[PDB]
Image (cartoon, rainbow, N blue to C red; front, top):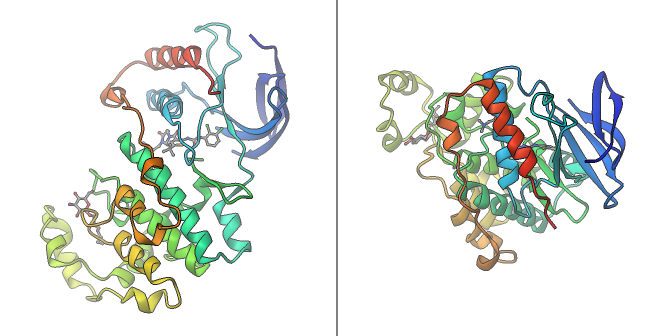
Length: 332
Ligand SMILES: CN(C)CCN1CCN(C(=O)c2cc(C(C)(C)C)sc2NC(=O)Nc2cccc(Cl)c2Cl)CCC1=O
Ligand SMILES: CCCCCCCCO[C@@H]1O[C@H](CO)[C@@H](O)[C@H](O)[C@H]1O
């Protein structure tokens, strides 16, 4: 069991093994960049804030540990290490997670290099590939946007969650529809891709209602087939009252873009989540012919998330979390 050492960073106490050097704040859990003096590579180390404060917190701690221990894909954050100072369960009250440091996020790439059609094809391919793997474990990202995308200098990408966000949110998450299918994340990819093509935020809503108005101006007011599914008496009368926007002709909107990009955008940015292309379908889209390889778009091992429907005690969440810390095997 390594020797730990205590350090102070922007008001936070950090106890990590010696192995991890040159800590410097990256944001606020909180996250430091560090040098792994054991393998020679830069890492990001996340310290979980108040992991066991609530039942909701204690569960979310367990969730994060479980999810990350299961993600083993090129385009999704992976776990290099997980550790705690605590030599036993009684002492246990802090959690740290370790991943590969990617040096920049996608907003950074976007505000200071105008991207080629070839770049957009590569970056969105990678999001979809990571997303196929995510979706096959039955997991929904729900908060996909450029700041949750890590990119290196070869423009290689991983999907992650640092925890407006609204600009990339599916209109149904902002109406609290509640079931949500995995294409919520495909609506996000549409917003990300549009902005990679344009250099501009597709939907810069000022707030929650402006967001929705902006979306409705692009895609139009809901079609009969969609109105049809609004089981809620509620919505329907309100929507029919609105300025009855027709769906904008996307070719006209994303003018000079590759026509396969446009066509892929029309298949992601559909109001009706039942009609949006899946991550799998999208990888087979002709827009990605240069990068597509059906033998190299792997799906995840079965993910046991029976724990999600469980209501347990803080002490149980914590002890479960501890066993997950103990059982961690690092990758090669
Ligand atoms: C209900 N719910 C889907 C929304 C809230 N979630 C967020 C999702 N989550 C997560 O923990 C989560 C899920 C992820 C995918 C993309 C695979 C979907 S990535 C990630 N966490 C993460 O990226 N951590 C991290 C980031 C930078 C540096 C370091 Cl060092 C690390 Cl450890 C688990 C916690 C929770 O409850
Ligand atoms: C302002 C009008 C925008 C509302 C967007 C509704 C489109 C979401 O799409 C809907 O999502 C649900 C999954 O949560 C599905 O159950 C519905 O069948 C599907 O049509």
